Image: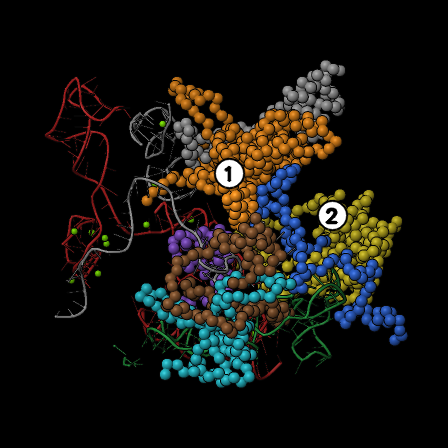
Chain colours: A yellow, B cyan, D blue, E purple, F orange, G brown, I red, J green
Amino acid sequence: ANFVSWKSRTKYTITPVKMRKSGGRDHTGRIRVHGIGGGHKQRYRMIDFLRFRPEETKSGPFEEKVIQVRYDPCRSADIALVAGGSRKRWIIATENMQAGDTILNSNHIGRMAVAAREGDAHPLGALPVGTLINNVESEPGRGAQYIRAAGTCGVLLRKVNGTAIIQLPSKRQMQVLETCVATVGRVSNVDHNKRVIGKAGRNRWLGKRPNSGRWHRKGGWAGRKIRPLPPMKSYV
Amino acid sequence: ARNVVYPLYRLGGPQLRVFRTNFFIQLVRPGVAQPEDTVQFRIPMEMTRVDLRNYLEGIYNVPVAAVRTRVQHGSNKRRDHRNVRIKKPDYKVAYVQLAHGQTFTFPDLFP
Amino acid sequence: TVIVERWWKVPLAGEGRKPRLHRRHRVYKLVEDTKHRPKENLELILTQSVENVGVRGDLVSVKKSLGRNRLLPQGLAVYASPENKKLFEEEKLLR
Amino acid sequence: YEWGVRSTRKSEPPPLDRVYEIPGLEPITFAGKMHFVPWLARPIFPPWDRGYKDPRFYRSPPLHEHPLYKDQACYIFHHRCRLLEGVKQALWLTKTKL
Amino acid sequence: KARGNEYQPSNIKRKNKHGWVRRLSTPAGVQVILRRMLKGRKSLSH
Amino acid sequence: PLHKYPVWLWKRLQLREGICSRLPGHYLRSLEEERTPTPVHYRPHGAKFKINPKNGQRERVEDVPIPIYFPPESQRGLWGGEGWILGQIYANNDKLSKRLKKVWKPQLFEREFYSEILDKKFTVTVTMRTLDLIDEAYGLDFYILKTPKEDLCSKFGMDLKRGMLLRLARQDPQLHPEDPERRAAIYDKYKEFAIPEEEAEWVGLTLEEAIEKQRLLEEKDPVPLFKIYVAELIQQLQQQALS
Amino acid sequence: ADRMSKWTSKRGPRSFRGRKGRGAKGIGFLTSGWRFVQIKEMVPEFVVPDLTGFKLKPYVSYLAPESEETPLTAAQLFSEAVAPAIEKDGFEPTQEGKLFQLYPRNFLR
RNA sequence: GCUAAACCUAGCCCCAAACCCACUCCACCUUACUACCAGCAACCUUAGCCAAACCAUUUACAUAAAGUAUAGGCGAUAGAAA
RNA sequence: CCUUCUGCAUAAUGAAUUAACUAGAAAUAACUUUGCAAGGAGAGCCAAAGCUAAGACCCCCGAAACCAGACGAGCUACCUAAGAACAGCUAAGAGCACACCCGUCUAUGUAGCAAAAUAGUGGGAAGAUUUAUAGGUAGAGGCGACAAACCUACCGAGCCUGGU
RNA sequence: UCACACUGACAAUUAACAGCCCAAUAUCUACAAUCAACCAACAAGUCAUUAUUACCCUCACUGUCAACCCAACACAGGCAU
Ligand SMILES: [Mg+2]
Ligand SMILES: [Mg+2]
Ligand SMILES: [Mg+2]
Ligand SMILES: [Mg+2]
Ligand SMILES: [Mg+2]
Ligand SMILES: [Mg+2]
Ligand SMILES: [Mg+2]
Ligand SMILES: [Mg+2]
Ligand SMILES: [Mg+2]
Ligand SMILES: [Mg+2]
Ligand SMILES: [Mg+2]
Ligand SMILES: [Mg+2]
Ligand SMILES: [Mg+2]
Ligand SMILES: [Mg+2]
Ligand SMILES: [Mg+2]
Ligand SMILES: [Mg+2]
Ligand SMILES: [Mg+2]
Ligand SMILES: [Mg+2]
Ligand SMILES: [Mg+2]
C-alpha cells in the first residue's frame, strides 16, 4: 500500500510543482470518491492565499504590482502572479486586473471608509457598507478560504461591534472578525458557468471519469426541499 | 585470497598485503585461433583483473600489459536417473596479452 | 471496574486444578457496576483553613473529586491514616 | 497556510519508555545486543561523530560557523538571474543612460 | 481470443511479489517459509 | 513416538536448563509462585458452601476468575485490576433470543500524582478503581509497595515499585542536601518491606529482562591464557623453591 | 521460471544483471557520471619473496622417517618460549594501536 | 515362445526407556546465497460443519464415585466435585 | 448378470480382460455352557436365585458449501510516474485508407494447428485510442462508460491448509 | 536408433553497447511542444543553478552463443522499439 502524497514542499516555491494525480485513491488503495481519474497532466503552482504577510524585516503596509495573468488548471478561476518588494507570490486574480496594475496591501483599520479599488485589500473595518468581496478568512491570520472560485463574490451586510457579517455567495450569513483581511471585487474568469463543454473529450481531459451504470432508484431525498436560510454561524 | 574475509579500508589505512595465496589459475589452448601474443587463463570466481595482473607480475614475472576477462556458463542440460539437472562449475576466462612482442606459442604435449 | 456475572455455571474442577472454560461460559451478564452507585465521602485531615469546609486540624468528609484535585495534590490535606492521626492528636493536645 | 504536510515530513519518533522517568536506576535496554529487539526498553544512544574526515561522506558546518560569514546580505548576480522588470532594472542598478 | 497464455514472464515482478524480503516483511511469508521448511522443500522462495 | 516430558513443562525445562538456571532464587521463586489475584469483574463467594436453593442440601462452590485481557495501554499505565472483558450477552437477557458478543472497556482518565520516595510528578492514565484503591491504601507509594505483582497487572507500576525498593535499600540522596531530617522522616515512614538491594534489583523484571541482566552481569572479556600460564609458572617456581 | 537454478548474474534483466554480480570483491567506488576510481590501497598486493637459493622442493623423498603428530597449541608454544620467563626469576595487553592485530582480522591470510 | 508374473533389502508403523539437532572455507534479510555508510515493526472471545429429521438455545476437541447431583425452545446433548 | 422395481437381453443403472487393494466395527437388554451360591465378583457393583464371563447384531464411494489463515492486478477492470505508436489522399473528439486495437457474417473443426484457430467480407486508426516498465485497489471483498460482467483456462462470487 | 535437433568430452561470448552513481549548509526553476520564425489556441504543459566547506586515490563488476519467449509439443495462437 505504497501511497506518498506529492504535497512535499516546505519552502514556498514559485515554479510549477509536479502534481501527481490520485484518481480517487487513498493511502490504502481503495476508491472512496467516484468520478476522478484519467486526465491530462498538470503542474500545481503554490498559491499564496494569505494576502497580508510582510516580508523579512518588514511590518508596515507595502504596495504591489501585476506582471501577468495566467490560467490555473487546478481550479476554475485564473491566477495572476504579483511581485511585492524583494519577492514574488502567486495569488488569485480579480476581475478587470490587467498587467501592470497597482495593488495596495494594508492592515490599518482607518477611522472612516477607504475607497478600495478592484484589486487591493483592506480589513473589513475600513470597507464601505455593501461591497462585493472575496477570499474571506475564517480567523485573524488564518488564510483565505471562503469565496475563491470564478465569479463568486460576497457582499458586505453590516458591522456589529468588532465583528462583521459577510453574505456568502450561497445566501448564507457568516460573522467574521473585523481585524481579518479580505480582498474586494469579484474573482476573474467571468462567464464560466456558461462555458459549454461540447463533448466528453474535454470532460475526460479535466479528469472526471463517467458516472456509474447502476440505475439508482430515486428515494425520498430526490424530491425538492424548499428549506429556509440557515442560522448565522459566527467564529467568536 | 579466495573465501577469506577482506579488511575494511577506511581512508588512512595501510596497503592491503596478501600473504599465502589461496586461489589458483591454469592456462589452456585457444580453440578459436587467437593472435600471436594473447594467453588464455581460467580465472576463478573470486578474482578480478588487476588482482590476476599483480599475481602474475609477482610470481611468474610475465610482462603483463592488457587483460580482458569474462564469465563462462557451464552447460546444465544433463539429467540423471532421478531427472535432476547437473549444473557444471562456472569458471571465469581471461585473455592476457604479453608486451615487448614476446610471442608465446602454445607447446604441444603428449607427442 | 464493571461487576459482571457468568452464565451456565461452572462444573467445578477439583481443588488444585484449573477449570477448562468454554464459549458457553464466555457469555457473561452485567449485574452491577462501580458507577451509578451512591458515592462515598472519604475522610481527609486538612492542614490549613480553606473556606468553611474544614478547620485546621479538624477532619471532615470532603468529596472525592475536590479531595483529589485541590486538597491532596496541593498538600492541603492528608489521608485518614492511623500514622498521622496520633501526631495530629498530640499536636491538638499540645495546643 | 503552513506548507509541509505531516505525512511528508519526518515521522515523529515514538514516545520514550516510561522506565527512564524513574530517578534513577539502570533501565535494562537492548544495548548489550547488536540488533533490534521488540521486548525490553529502548536506549538513548549518544550523537556519534566520525573521527577522520571522508571526502565521500563529509558533512559541512551550519551557516552560523564560517570563515567570512557577514551580516550584510549581499545580492549576487549570475547568468541564471532572470530579471523581472527588464532594462530599467539594469539601468537603475548600473546608473547609466540608455 | 487465445486465453491459453495467462503467464507473462518477468523477473522483476516475480522477485517483488514472491520475494524473500517481501515474505519476511510480514508474518505471512514467515509462516509460509516455516511451513515449506517443515515440509522439506528444496526451494523456499523465488 | 511420545514425548519424555509434557507440553506444559517445556517452560520449566528451559528455565532449569542453562542461562535461566544461573538466575537468582528469589526471582525464580516469585516467577514460579503464580498466585490467584483479587476478584474484580465478579463478586466472590463468602464461604465454600452456600446451600443451593430448590434442594435443601449443601454443595461446595468456587469462584472462577475472568480470563480478562491486558492491552499495551494497561501495561504502559497504572491500572488497578480491571481490563478488557471480551464476553457475550443475549438480546433481552434471555437465552431464547439471539447470542451476540461484547467487548467491555474500562474508564480511563489522566490525573497527576506525587511520590515522596522518588520526588517526581507523573502523568499516568489512572482509572476509578485505581484511585479508589490508592485512597484506601493512603498514599500512592504505600499502594504500590503493598500490591504484589500479579494483582498489579502492569509494567510501569512494577518498575516504579522496583525503583522505590532500590531507593529504600541504597538510601541514596533523594532530596539533595539541605534536607536531612525530611529525608530521614520519609525513609522511616516506610520502615516496612525494606527489601535488600541484591533482591530489589530483580523485582518486576520479565524473563527476557532477567536473561539480559544475567548476560550483562557475567559478561566481561575472556582472560588471556598467557596470564594463566604465567601464574602456573610462578606457582611451579614457588613449589620448587619450597622443596 | 525454475526454482532450483541458483540465482546468479544470468537471470535478471539489464538492471538486475548490472547491480548483481559474482563474489569477486570490489576494488574501489563509483562517483560522478559513471567514473569508477581505483584505490591502490584496496588493490591486493601479493608479497612474493625471492626463491633464489631455496633448497626445498614441493615433493618429499621416501627415505624420510615417520614421526607422530604433535598438535601445536598455546601450552607448547609457551613451554618452548620459556627461557626468558625463567631467566627473569614480551606481552601486549591492548593491541588497538597495532598494525597486525590478532583478534580483529585486519590482515589477509 | 514373444510380450509378460516369482523372488528381501531398503524402509516403515505400534510401544518401553531417555528430554533431541543446530560454526570445513565464505554469503544469508537489498533482487537470501550480494564485503564496504545517517531510522514505524507482536502482546485481540476462534469460527463453522454436524446433531436436535429444519434451526434461530445448545453441541466434547489409573479405576470407582457416575453417567449421580445439575444445565438444557428442561431435548437433542453436556457434565463434575466431596 | 446386479437392482431401483407388481416387472428387464429388453430399446432401464453399471461393465474389454488379468493383477492386487476395496466395502458391517461398539451399547442397554437377551442366547450361552463354564466357577460359586443367599451370596456373587481381585475394594467400588448386583441381589424375593443371582453374580462373574468367552462367543454373537450394527459398511464403502458419491454433492451443492461456509468458517480463520496465507496468493493473487505478470491475462482481465480501475488508478499512479516516466516513454513509444499512428504512411498517404481530400480538408472539426472531419472522411477514406498503411502499420496497429476490436471481431457483425460466410465455410472448415469441435480430441481441431488452437481447452476459442484459419481466408475474405468488417468498425476505429490525431484520440474518451493502442502499447513497453514498475507500483497500488482481493472474497463478510476489489473493480465496473452496469456485462450483477471480470479478479491466472469452470466466479450469482477462486484457489490450498484444518474443521471434510 | 519420414529418415540420419539423442548421449559422454571439447570452448566460444572478452566492452568501448546499458547499467553498477553523484557529500553536505541554505537560495534561485512564470513567458510550452507542435521545422517555432507569422497566425492560431486549450487538454495550461516532458529536460536548467548559486557562495562556501572537503576532495587532484582513476578504467574494476554484470550479458555479450544459438534455430531462443509465453500456450502440455518442433503448435496456422500473442509480442514493443
Ligand atoms: Mg450525471
Ligand atoms: Mg443511469
Ligand atoms: Mg476427584
Ligand atoms: Mg441438523
Ligand atoms: Mg453381486
Ligand atoms: Mg417403472
Ligand atoms: Mg439388443
Ligand atoms: Mg440393457
Ligand atoms: Mg439408477
Ligand atoms: Mg435411471
Ligand atoms: Mg455403456
Ligand atoms: Mg454465503
Ligand atoms: Mg495492471
Ligand atoms: Mg476521426
Ligand atoms: Mg474511419
Ligand atoms: Mg441491467
Ligand atoms: Mg466430501
Ligand atoms: Mg547477439
Ligand atoms: Mg494450449
Q: Name the residue under label 2.
A: A173
Between residue F194 and residue B16, name the one nearer to us. B16
Please provide percent x and percent y for residue F60: 41, 23
Label 1 is placed on what type of residue? Leu
The image shows residue J52, relative to residue G94, as above or below, that is: below
| Label 2 Cα crowd, 10 Å radius (few <14 / some 14-19 / many 20+) | many
Residue at figure coordinates x 77%, y 50% from the top left? A141
Q: Residue at x 87, y 69 (%)?
A: D92
Q: Mark 1 points at which residue?
A: F23
Q: Position of residue E45 (x, y in %)?
A: 45, 59
The answer to whether one can see residue B44 in this image is yes
* Label 1 residue SS: loop
Task: Please identify the quadrant where the C terminus of chain B is shown.
Answer: bottom left
Residue A192 visible somewhere in the drawing: no
Label pair 2/1, CB-CB below 8 angstroms? no
Q: Which chain carries label 1?
A: F
Packing grade of label 1 (10 A; few <14, some 14-19, many >=20) is some
Nearer to us in this view, A109 or F185: F185
Mark nearest the camera among 2 and 1 is: 1
Tag 2: residue type? Gln
